[PDB]
Structures are given as structure tokens and as C-alpha cells.
Image (tube, coloured by chain):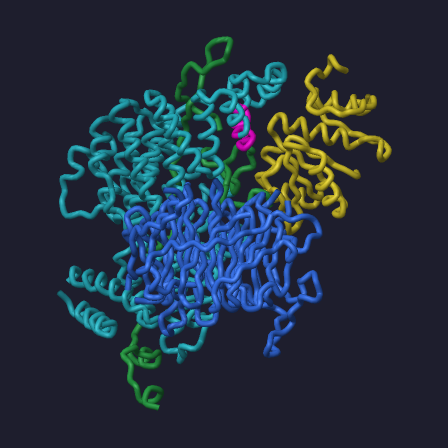
Chain colours: A blue, B yellow, C cyan, D green
Amino acid sequence: SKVFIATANAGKAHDADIFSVSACNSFTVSCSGDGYLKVWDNKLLDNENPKDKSYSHFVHKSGLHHVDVLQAIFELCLVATTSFSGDLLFYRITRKKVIFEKLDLLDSDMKKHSFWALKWGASNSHRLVATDVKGTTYIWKFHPFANWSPTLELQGTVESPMSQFATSVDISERGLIATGFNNGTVQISELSTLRPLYNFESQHSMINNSNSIRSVKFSPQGSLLAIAHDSNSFGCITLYETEFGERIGSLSVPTEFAHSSWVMSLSFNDSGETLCSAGWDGKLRFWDVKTKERITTLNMHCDDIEIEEDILAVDEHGDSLAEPGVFDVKFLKKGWRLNESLCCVCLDRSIRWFREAG
Amino acid sequence: EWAHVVFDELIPNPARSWPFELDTFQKEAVYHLEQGDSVFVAAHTSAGKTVVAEYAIAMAHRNMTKTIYTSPIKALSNQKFRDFKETFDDVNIGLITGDVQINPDANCLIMTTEILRSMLYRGADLIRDVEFVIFDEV
Amino acid sequence: KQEESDSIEWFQSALRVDPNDVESWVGLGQAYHACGRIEASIKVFDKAIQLRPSHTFAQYFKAISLCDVGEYLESLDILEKVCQEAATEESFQIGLVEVLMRCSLDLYSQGFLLKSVSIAKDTIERIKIIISELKCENQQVWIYLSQVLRLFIWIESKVDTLPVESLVSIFENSEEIDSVDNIKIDTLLDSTTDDNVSIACKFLILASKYSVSAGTVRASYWYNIGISELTAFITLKEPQYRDAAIFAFKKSIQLQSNTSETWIGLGIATMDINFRVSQHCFIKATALEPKATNTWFNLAMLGLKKKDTEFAQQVLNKLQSLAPQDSSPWLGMALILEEQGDIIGSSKLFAHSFILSNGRSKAAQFMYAKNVLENHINNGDDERDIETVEKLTTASIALEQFFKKSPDSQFALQCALLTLERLHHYENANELANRLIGILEKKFQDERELFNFAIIKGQFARIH
Amino acid sequence: IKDRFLRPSNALPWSLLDMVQDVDYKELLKVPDPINRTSYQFKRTGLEGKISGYKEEVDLKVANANASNSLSITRSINHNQNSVR
């Protein structure tokens, strides 16, 4: 958890900003503002260009900003994504080309809502959670069989504690749901009952309204919750304890703040001992959960691309992309791609993969 | 409190086996290690002094204790790490340097002598379970 | 014969002939644990359990050895399963109680103040089950009960979750000092109009006194009684507990005068009556155990109590040269400098003490918050200054952590209201101001009380 | 112009706050910890070497020995401290 080596790379992957990424055992899927959905095969060989093993599908003219993938053993592989207009779209992945099957799982009354965020909950029935621009969270149960015959069953909704924009959502393996809002408030509710449990506000001050939750994550053990939020042009991370709902501390570094510009995404490793954060300042930082101390830092440059023709030094307006901000980051379990792995997407329209030494 | 200057029935349960046959000095080192004593080996390079180290690592692994390998050259730690990780199976290998830590909770840790001296002066808890310490390039 | 370093070779030799001998594995792991090789012992006990999954002593030993490296979840799971399997052996029950107590103490140390109280209640429940149903009793269980009963006094915001019924059941199921402190089960809860902190302190005293079996155990028994009475006297501030502590400490010193903690306790006990005897006791304690830095801090604070600034400064300089990682010397230096008249150095030392404390001292948090508030009231600042806002935020967090342990503190509540009104945090200010207004209303007929009430009401109107 | 120059607010700025705001030695000490001087000793009976019972006895080993005041290998372990360095 201290040495990371670059493994594979791909430049100019999309025609617009790559807003999110997700991964499973078989492949890595990314979305972008051009409206396409791309699949990157995880099982590669030596010195094989990742753009050779890639499959794209057009989804919506408006563009996409959220994506998630569900893989479970009959083998089903589902993808759910959200578009800029506010639609919720489900696709089934089948393999040696890749086949995209559009699924119509939402009824007519459920197609009038504008969705922002989404997340899959795998069985340990599978569940789907989503947030609304009005500040509501919806809970679904997914039934694949009745023979292939998928149905989505609505379980209930959770209203906003105060209404504000719901920006992020997560679900734990012990049956908890966390929702983040645009004023810095986080609500935690019970999965089996749909009744809220805790409600804590993480703002340094309320003099100005530039506080907003950007990411909420549950520990792999499920006993911890990490929150990334804004502090008027700074990025902050705070750790909470989910069994009783009390503040533990904060992650900070000289630059009371974790990042210099903004913290976009969070991610835990398999054991829940290390946390990684992605910053608008163009850095990845790794933290020790028990000691609350920084471990390592990675720097992003436009010159990291292996192929020199795919290096995007400037955008269409002439602004420099020498140190581009990171949109999203993801940990990959062992054996998906010996040791763990990591993936991230940046402002230079690149997708990058890393490997842990050991 | 003294120093002394110096097979199938003597050691019927060896902790490691090799395709070839060990030389006399290798057998003597293995036998005296099994009896429970310390050993000083002085031989030409590429005569097979790494067999003694490998046998010590395997023997400590059997007892469920730890081994530390040290050298005074900082450019040999990485080579030794790679070589030991290639040689051994079911035995973990780690590497400790000034900044990086790889597999801290391993069975065989590789470092330099200055790191070990700092650990000894600072009372590191790692030494609680260490049974053998190997000094190379004396 | 209890010479465990000599049996390691024999157990290894026995295992070299028959690698499937479970009893040899258990013996070898027990020898490693006795010699200070905890991780190797854990590996050996895991191997023994793998060979025979029905072995209960291997599981008990593995859980006990896992408790020694700070892995309480796995150890508690193993011990709960073992106690559910064989529920008639007292050894497993006492082991479970010990692991629960140690887990709660570690959680308190690491800042998880809310989980520690629940684990303390669970430990009390297990102790009650043991004492009542299993009809067993030894010194260890009472020692554990006394150790775990202090978390209800330290975390005073959760003292209302004290299991009084289980405690009276445990004490009812089971003379020289009873005339000094007058603590008796027959007349413990009789007196009304007292908080739960007093009840917890009395239960701690009773638990210390009930732990009865070359005269080392008797001396330790009297020392524990003295320490419990000292804690009760410090918390409640009543004369009758100081005399009981002095009695117990004198008896323990008579039984064995070679121990340093007894002299430390005796010095703390008489620290207000006679400073010469306290100084003598602290000096003897330093002589007996010279690698202890708390005696030097006690002596420096005693010097500060009688207004001897230079003596305290010299002792604190020595202490800083001896234990830099501690936060107490920095707090003492900051107090001396603040009394002298320096402002910048006092602020720097208070900040260093607060940072070094890492949430383990209430005094550090309170002093840091007071200093930050005192430097930024009429200093001519603007909301656009990032550093001032961050200082105020840190002070607010420190005061919240302080209130988790010692609520109903008037000065801390006033400082918290002053900071919150300036950070625009009005709901927390409303709650804290309601608490403070209730406190001041209960506390009141004088003149300064009315003026303080008027000022508090003005701030409370500002909050609305 | 009206919103930027002539709109009063109910949140008091720091200037008005500056205009209107007005701002035991034994509790600094550490009481020593309790001492326990007893333990279980497990006994065996038989050639197989199975544990037959246990008794509570006195242990001949200072009581609260940690890494700050003892050099013995049997002292307590502080797992919040770095175990490698």
C-alpha cells in the first residue's frame, strides 16, 4: 500500500469529459459526455494496446455522467447509467464480441423522474439505489428469473431530512444507506426498514454556502464511513463511525485540508485499511485509516500517455492540461486484472491503470 | 560460550530438499543448525552459501518463527527480494527500507544493517518472534 | 515447574517425530506465549485448531493470545463460541470478561467514547451471570469489574446508562475501613438527591473492597482500595475519602514498602494538607522507580500550587528533557508563561500541547479553546481570513470532544456559545444555550448571578 | 444596487460581534492504575498430556511493565505504536 506502478494507458478515449468509471471481474466500463458507453476488457496480455480490446455503444445524445456494473453467478452482467437529461437506462452485457441488450425495467410512472446518482447492492436479492433532483432516494429489488425474465420491484422511498439536491449515495453490506446533499448534510437510514438512523452535518462554517457533499463511501467491513466535501475552494475528508454515529477525525496535509482544490471521489481497498482520494488539483493521495496520516501521493500529467499521438496537451480553447484533475478513482480486487489494482479517469480524456508492488 | 572449528539417518526430516547433492560443508552447516547452534561460513562466492540461508529460512518457517536477512549494500536488497520470492513457495518475503514497506507481516524480512540497528535501539516489536538473523558480506 | 524457555526444544523435538501431536502443539504455543512470542503462539494455536477443530483449550489460548495484539473482534467471536459450547467452566467465562474489559479500555483510549460504554455494560452483564449463576468468585473478576466501572465516571455524558440492578444483584449474591468512608451495601442507595456519578464512585469503592481472597497480595489489595478511594475523593471532593485513602496507603506501605505507586498515591493524598510530606513521598517514589515521569510532573504541580515558579520551571525543563512526547510539560510551561505575562510563547506552547495530546486530555482542549477565543475577540478580523476561521473551527471541535466527557461546565459552555455565534452555527448554539440557561436557572439569590443571567439572555436573544 | 448596498441582514458580522461580545491543580494529575498479582496455572495428568484442571496462584514477574519503563521481553505490547520501526 506504498508503491504503485503504472500498467496500461489510453489517451483520447472519449470525445468529451469522462465523468465516471466502474469495474467488475470481466471488464471496466466508462461513460462520457459524448453519449457513448465503452467496455475495456480486464484480462489483457503483455504489450497489448487497450484500445484494441474495447467495445463502444451509443446510449443518449445528451451524455452520461454515472455508471455502475453488477456481476453475479447462469451468468448475468448488468450495467445501469444516468444521462444528463435525467433518464435511468439498463443494459445487459453478453459475450468473442460484446452484445448490448437494452432492458425496459421501469414502468411508465417511474420514467417521469430525473435521476442523478445510482449504485448496485449485490447479494451476500440484489438491490438498486438512486437519488432524485428533488432529494429522494428510491430502493429496488432485482429479480432475474420468474427462464430469463427480469423485473424491478419498488421497495420504498426515503425523503430528504430538510428539500435540497441529493448528490451521492452508497449502500453497505450490512444493510445501511448513506445519502449526501448539497448543503453538507448526510443522512443514514436502515435498508430493511427504510427508517433514518443518523443525521450529521459536516461544515467548517456556515458563513458562506460553498459546502457540498461530493462522495460518501462505506468501509468494506461496513463499520466506517468516509465523506468528501467542499470548503470554499478547498477539499476536505472526514471519517465517521457508523455503529453509533460519532466523528472520528479528519484527513489533512500542509498545502487542515486534504486536497488543494476539491475532492471528487473516494475508494477503499479490499481490507479497508487504506483510502484513496482524487482531487481537482491533479493528485491522488493515499491515507492510513487507523493513524489518519498520509502515506503516498501520485501526480497526473498529460505526458503519461504511452502513445505520443494521443497526448492532449491543450483543450479546444488553448488552456493547458499539463496537470489535469481526476474525475473518478476505483480499486480493483485481487485477480481481476497477484495484488490489487487501481483505475482513474482525468480531464485529458485519458483512462489509466496502476498496480500495487508486492 | 565457545567457538568450534569443524546423513540420511542424522536428519530424517529435512526442512528443505534440493535436486542435487549438498557438499560436505553444506551438510555440516545444516546439521549444526538442526542441533540448535550458530554457524559462521567462509567460502568462495558461487560455492553454494545461499543453500544455508534458504535452509535456515525454511527451518524457521517450520517452527513458525521469523528470519531477518541483512546486507551492508543497499543495491542488493531488491535483488535478494526478487530472488527469494522466486525461490520460495508458501513462504512470504518482505522488504523494509527507509521509506517503502512491502509485506510487513511476512516470514522473512530483508533490510540493511543500519535499519536493523535503528530497530534495535528503538525497541521494535518485530524482534520478538525473530529466531535467526543472517549477516551477509561480512 | 514454570521454566518455559527450557521446554521449547523438547516440544520441537517431539513434534519432529509426530507432526500430528495436538498436545505437543498446545504445549509449544503455551511456551512461546510465556516467553514473549505472541504472534508465533497465535500461529501455533491456529495449527492446533486446524488439526482438531473440537479442541476447546486451543481456542481459548488462541483468543487470549489474540487479545495481546489488539484484535478484539476475532478474539471475542472465538471466546463467545467457546463459552456457548462449554458454559460450565469458569476459566472461559473469566477469559471472556477480561477480553471485554481490555477491548473497552482500548476503545476509550483511541477516542471511541460511545462504543466503550456499551462494551462496559456487556462486561458487567457477563460478570453478573458468572457471579450469580456459576457461583464462582476470585480476585480477578472483581479487579476487572473495578477497572470497567471507571469508564462510567470518565465519560460523564453516559453515566445515566449505569446498570444499577445488575450491580446490586452481583453484590448481594456474594470492617476496619468501613468506619472511615461508611460505604456499605445495606445503606448504599438509601441516600436520595445525589447524581449517578456518586453512585458509580461508591460502586467502584465497593468493588475494590470486595476483592478478597510473602504478603504481596494483601498489600496489592490495600493499594487498590486506596487508589479507588483517591479517585472517589478527586471526583466528589469530600474529606472522608481522603482519610480512607491515607489509611489504605499506610497499611499497604506497612505490608510492603518496596513499591513506588503506593508512595505516589500517598503523596497525591496529602498534597493539600502538608506539602513537606508530599514532597518527601514524591522524592522517595522517584528513587524507587526512576524511569517514571509522572512523579516529576506531580512535584512540579505541587511547586506551582504553593507559588514557587522557578522550582516548577526547573522541574519542567528536566521533564521536557526526559519525556518530550508527553503533553503535560508543555501545558505546565504554558501556564507559567501565561502567569508571567507573555502572550505569543504561551499561545505557541498551548498549541503544541493540544496537538501532542491527540484528544486524550480535557485540560489541553479547554486551554487551547480559551486561548484561541482570547486572541480573536477584539483583534479586528474579517470573515475572509482563512486562518482565523480554521482556528475557530478547530476550537469548536475541541470543545465538542471536551463536552463528550465533562458536560455541565459553565465556562466551557460560554466559550462554545461565543465561538458558535461567530461561526454562524445557530442550532448547536441553541442546544448549548438551552443547557446553560437551565444550569444557571437551577443554580439560583445574589447580584452577580443576575448580571451573568442578563448577559446570557442577551446572547440567547442574539441567537434567536 | 439594492441587494449589494442597501439590504440589511439578520446575521451579525464580525464587526458588530466585536462591538458587543464580551469574553484545580489535582485534576491535572494522573492517578496510578490498579495492580493484579494472580493468574491461572493449567495442569496436566496422563501420558497423552491433556489439561486436567487449573488453579489460581501468584506470579513472580514489576506488575504493569510496558515499553517505557522495562527492558524485559515479557513486557506489554503497545499495538498503537509502529511495530516495524
Query: Toward which corner of the image does residue C225 lie, by quadrant?
Result: top left
Outermost residue to the front: A147
Q: Position of residue A319 (x, y in %)?
A: 60, 77
Q: Which residues are magenta?
A: C29-42
Residue at (53%, 59%) from the top-left corner? A57
Q: Is residue C458 magenta?
A: no
Spot occupied by residue A147 in the image (x, y as percentages of width and height): 41, 41
Of residues D13 and A108, the one nearer the viewer is A108
Residue at horizontal 75%, vertical 23%? B30
Q: Nearer the viewer, residue C204 or B84?
A: B84
Tell me the quarter of the image containing the C terminus of chain A: top right
The image shows residue C312, relative to residue C170, as above or below, that is below
Residue C331 in the image, given as x and y percentages of width and height? 44, 58
User: What residue appears at the point 45 percent right and 70 percent down from the top-left corner?
Assistant: C342
How many labels sit on residues? 0
Residue most extreme to the bottom: D1
Prevailing secondary structure of the magenta residues:
helix
Asked if residue C36 is among those painted magenta in the image, a careful observer would answer yes
Front in this rendered view, residue C47 or A326: A326
One can see residue C400 in this view: yes
Q: Is residue A92 left or right of residue B91?
A: left
- Image check: C358 left or right of B23? left
**Closest to the observer: D40 or B10?**
B10
